[PDB]
Amino acid sequence: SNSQLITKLNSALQIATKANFYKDRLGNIEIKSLDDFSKLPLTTKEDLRKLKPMEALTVDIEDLFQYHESFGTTGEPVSTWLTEKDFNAYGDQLNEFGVNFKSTDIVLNRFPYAISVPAHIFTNAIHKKGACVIPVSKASAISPLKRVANLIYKLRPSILTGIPDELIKLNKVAKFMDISLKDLGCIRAICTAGEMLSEGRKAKLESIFGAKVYNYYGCTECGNMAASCDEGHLHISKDFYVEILDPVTLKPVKEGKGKIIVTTLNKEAFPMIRYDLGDIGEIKYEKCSCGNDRPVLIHHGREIDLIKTSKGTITFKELQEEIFKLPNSVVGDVFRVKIQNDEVIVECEADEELDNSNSNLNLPIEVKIKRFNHGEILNIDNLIEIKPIAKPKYVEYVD
Amino acid sequence: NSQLITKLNSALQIATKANFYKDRLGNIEIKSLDDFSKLPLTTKEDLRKLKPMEALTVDIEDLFQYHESFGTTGEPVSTWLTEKDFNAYGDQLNEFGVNFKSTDIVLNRFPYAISVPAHIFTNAIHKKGACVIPVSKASAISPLKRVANLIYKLRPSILTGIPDELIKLNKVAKFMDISLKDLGCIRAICTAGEMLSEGRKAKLESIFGAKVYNYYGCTECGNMAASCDEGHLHISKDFYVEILDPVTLKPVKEGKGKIIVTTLNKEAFPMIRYDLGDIGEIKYEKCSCGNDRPVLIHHGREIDLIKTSKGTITFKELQEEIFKLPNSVVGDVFRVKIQNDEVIVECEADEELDNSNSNLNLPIEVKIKRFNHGEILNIDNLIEIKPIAKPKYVEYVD
Ligand SMILES: [Mg+2]
Ligand SMILES: [Mg+2]
Ligand SMILES: [Zn+2]
Ligand SMILES: [Zn+2]
């Protein structure tokens, strides 16, 4: 049934248009098809920024339950009220695919509970299956990586969750503490989210931790649009309608990569009608061997993370996919990307310098691997510090 | 008493599931509070020596949350919780305290990192249908400047945070030309995690123009007590509180003493006669609030006692007298130095006090040393905003 999906898209509009923002550019216009839908104006990040938090609201103050934002201080941020239902929906989305949380599971939650949502909805999800949350958080004086390393050694949790960046550092700090988190033999699964994950970097994470990885694709304003199957592919949540548009035309593509627009099927506080995530990807419709009937998504990363020389363009994913076919000797787990004077330079902490003259990348553009020394791009001494913290110290005996 | 005694016994029967408690309590029953008071105290330093699996009376399946001493300075105390237990903690916050309505938007300035107050306040607030703004604390993500803007923008109806932070919040905000009081949106405050004199409570109320509710709790127990409308803490029904003599360690007949607590309603690892290391006293005069539960007077930590040769006072008693002085000579920023057998209170304030004819109505000598605003507490340290964003892996050069 398109009949259902179309019923839903319409509901979403009827709620949305409770709010000035949505009414003064969608009125009471109904729709009869996806194509008639695709005629409707996109909703941009920069649109929502201009909104007071009371302008980003389709429910009564009474139904408010949580609040969230852009964690980033760089750029005006986006109010995202949630009702209990909405919050609970987000959580269910994490459970819809992803790893199978058991009650016997103890889960180290390394996502920031400060203002972001992934921390909170993962908790929601995990509690739902009867498992235990260790609220370590992130970017808190309270829980630097040394402590997290000790926490894992001590508590032996069965699942780690954290943005793949932090998880790579965690393993570095821990290895500098003479701890192989992998050999503990207690971590069966990982939950990455908050940055795009190549199959190459996913396979890196799996080799480090010796665990299966489940990746979760979401955002504050929407919820969690997709997550990994056992086979490794993201799948799209039933609570969303995902379109792939052409960067320039802004029309549905016939196939292949494109801008990722999402509409909320199941969020009532302020629904996302055709929201421009600003990412790149593609929906496949071949049924995954996992057996799940929902459609697979290939995430190519953010739009600004496209690699554009004169001689072509590639997605950050495509770049990464090729980087990480090279040995760890030449690439490693710490890298950044400079595009300058019409060349692509990947700077990598690694032991060996690469031929480059015999690099033999299978990309439509030229990419060089510039070698660095471990610790030069990522300073380990910055991560190992522990600030002592406690309650205020008001009463001093000078003895 | 038959109820309370039934409960104390249950607590022991669970507790002794754990070697820690069994190898010093066996299956000993009790018939009275007095027979209870014969049992060995449980100390902070006791629990520290426990592996997290040794601090556990339930199966891994029933585990739900985990927590610790937030400080990275000093070995920490494992505190598992089951869903029930967590839910109990929350209910304790709701048992007295402020009355959370569904029309309430609450800025939650407690750290969600490892501590519990942040999480159980959320629990409580959701329970009444109100909205949580999870600002947290000690996170790069949420410096005071942002919190000030967040309040200006979202106009929340309730702030929650340790009174120290809340005093700073108002400083940072006032330096940003924002009077949080004149917003007209904050009706209530929820202090916790440090002791609160009636004088400092009244200070907070003057700053924010809101009523204060204080909450007295700890990670291992839950939240043992919270304020009534009248101002007085009351003890939660989920706990048995004793006041012991500092030296003898026997029930006192009346007055101040060491505060020991037993968990009536926590099953993962119950606190049997736990030494908080605080000082206080139970009154049984009924508060005019009409709540029948007994009032508690919190005097602060033991190490925060003021001991000269010429006597001794509680941090509260000291504070209570400090803050009867004009605002001109005592503000909201103070510290306490005891040196060469004198008590010096250093205060940011405009006027110097005529200590040569000082009022102070205490059994010991206490001098008020005047300082300039911003010299004890540097506002410039707090106004910084650290830029944070996702990782930045792709750079276009030039
Ligand atoms: Mg469990
Ligand atoms: Mg509400
Ligand atoms: Zn699949
Ligand atoms: Zn009362």
Image (cartoon, coloured by chain):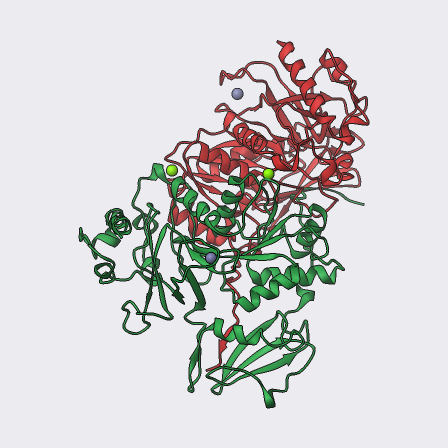
Chain colours: A red, B green
Q: Is residue B130 above or below residue B194?
A: above
Q: Is residue A185 left or right of residue A338?
A: left
Q: Disc count in the image?
A: 0
Q: Quadrant of residue B351?
A: bottom right
Nearest the eye: A331 or B50 = B50
From the top left corner, tell me how far across and down residue A305 is, in percent.
71, 36
Quarter of the image for the N terminus of chain A: give it. top right
Q: Is residue B35 left or right of residue B339?
A: left
Q: Is residue A179 visible?
A: no
Q: Is residue A309 left or right of residue A71?
A: right
Quarter of the image for the C terminus of chain A: give it. bottom left
Q: Is residue A185 above or below residue B285?
A: above
The residue under the point 61% across, 66% down is B203
From the top left corner, tell me how far across and down residue B146 is, in percent.
68, 52
Nearest the eye: B203 or B284 = B284
Q: Quarter of the picture for ligand 2? A: top right
From the top left corner, tell me how far across and down residue A207 is, in percent.
47, 36
Nearest the eye: A381 or A225 = A225
Q: Is residue B42 above or below residue A216?
A: below
Q: Is residue B211 visible?
A: yes
Q: Quadrant of residue A269?
A: top right
The residue under the point 52% across, 36% down is A122
Q: Is residue B89 left or right of residue B266?
A: right
From the top left corner, tell me how far across and down residue A146 is, in percent.
48, 54
Nearest the eye: B146 or B48 = B146
Q: Residue furthest bottom?
A: B356
